[PDB]
Amino acid sequence: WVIP
Amino acid sequence: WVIP
Amino acid sequence: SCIQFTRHASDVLLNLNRLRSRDILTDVVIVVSREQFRAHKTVLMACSGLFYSIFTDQLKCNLSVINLDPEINPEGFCILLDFMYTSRLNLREGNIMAVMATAMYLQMEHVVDTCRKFIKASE
Amino acid sequence: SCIQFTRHASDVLLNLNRLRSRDILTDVVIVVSREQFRAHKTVLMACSGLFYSIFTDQLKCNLSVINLDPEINPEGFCILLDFMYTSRLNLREGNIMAVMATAMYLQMEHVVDTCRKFIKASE
Ligand SMILES: N#Cc1cnn2c(Nc3ccc4c(c3)CC(=O)N4)cc(Cl)nc12
Ligand SMILES: N#Cc1cnn2c(Nc3ccc4c(c3)CC(=O)N4)cc(Cl)nc12
Ligand SMILES: [Cl-]
Ligand SMILES: [Cl-]
């Protein structure tokens, strides 16, 4: 999971 | 396009 | 000896979401209490262990309407359906419990994982 | 304020290809001369300007069989259909002309681009  |  | 187009999978998903927004080729309505959500069976199966089980069933595969458990929260389902079609999860303090419970029911293991990690950090 | 699951789009595409291999929920047969290819209309529209035009048409959207131009090569179509479902293009010296011509017909601009660059390097 990432900060887009 | 890339070499997978 | 194949070559690969990096953005292809993301571009496919973006167009599947465009089809959902325009209601093109949607073949099922998911009923969550008083709310209705139109979707593509193939996308639902591709994202969820629950829908994969439902739509591989020789009788349920032909249903145009699927009713979810009355305990399922419509907003939680809406957030997860948006995630299915975009890879983006609108996870907030006010909705995290509903999102995690819906993800457990839908058998969306990666979403369950992250909801667990976000709750653990707040305790 | 969304979070994003990097591998989600690739995982969706992998499961759509699994559905194609098992012939689950395929709703169209593409006829290319003596050969037949089963596929999902939604995936075909998402990858190709030609199929996007065909399946948004109020009459053609309901067809279970689509016949392509007799000049279209079945192997070229097969390579492009595999690409649609996997992001991988089996581009070889022996098939590049057929792949490029099929990609132009299917309106798959990124494939056309690369076929052009690969031909230019060999001349
Ligand atoms: N054919 C086919 C096919 C279509 N969909 N699909 C799967 N869908 C699925 C099943 C379980 C889970 C998820 C997705 C996300 C998750 O957390 N669990 C799996 C397989 Cl092994 N095959 C297929
Ligand atoms: N709704 C919808 C929807 C479904 N599919 N789709 C598009 N599919 C497409 C159209 C043209 C081209 C390609 C894909 C690859 C290419 O080279 N050209 C576009 C839009 Cl703007 N919208 C949609
Ligand atoms: Cl997931
Ligand atoms: Cl393309």
Image (cartoon, coloured by chain):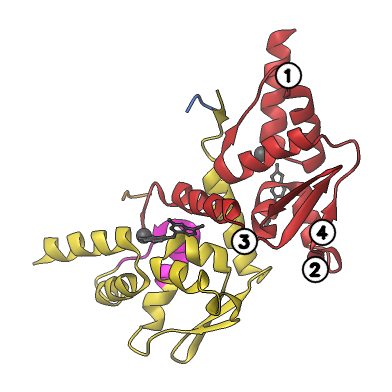
Chain colours: A blue, B orange, C red, D yellow
Cα separation between marks 1 and 4: 29 Å
Report the residue marked by disc 3.
D18
Is ligand 3 within 8 Å of the beta carbon of the residue shown at mark 1?
no
Give x and y (percent) for residue D67.
47, 86
Q: Position of residue C7 (x, y in %)?
A: 40, 47
Q: Main secondary structure of the magenta part?
A: helix
Mark 3 lies within 8 Å of ligand 1 (Cβ measured): yes
Q: Amino acid at mark 4?
A: Val
Say if mark 2 contacts mark 3, CB within 8 Å: no
* Residue at the disc numbered 1: C94
- The chain containing the residue under callout 4 comes to C
Q: Which mark sits nearer the N-terminus, 1 or 4?
A: 4
Are labels 4 and 3 on one chain? no
Q: Quadrant of residue C73?
A: top right
Identify the residue at horizontal 53%, vertical 40% (top origin): D7
Q: Is mark 4 within 8 Å of ligand 1?
A: no
Q: Is residue C42 left or right of residue D47?
A: right
Q: Position of residue C20 (x, y in %)?
A: 60, 53
Instruction: Identify the residue at horizontal 90%, vertical 43% (top origin).
Output: C69
Q: Which residue is mark 4?
A: C65
For badge 2, the amino acid type reads Asn
Specify whether disc 2 shares its chain with disc 1: yes
Q: Crowding at label 2, few (<14), some or many (≥20) Cα neighbours within 10 Å?
A: few
Mark 2 falls on what kind of element? helix
Same chain under badges 2 and 4? The reply is: yes
Residue D90 on the magenta segment: yes
Q: To which chain does the residue with label 1 belong?
A: C
Q: Where does label 2 land, which residue?
A: C62
For the question of whether residue C109 can be seen, the reply is: yes
Measured Cα–Cα span from mark 2 to mark 1: 36 Å
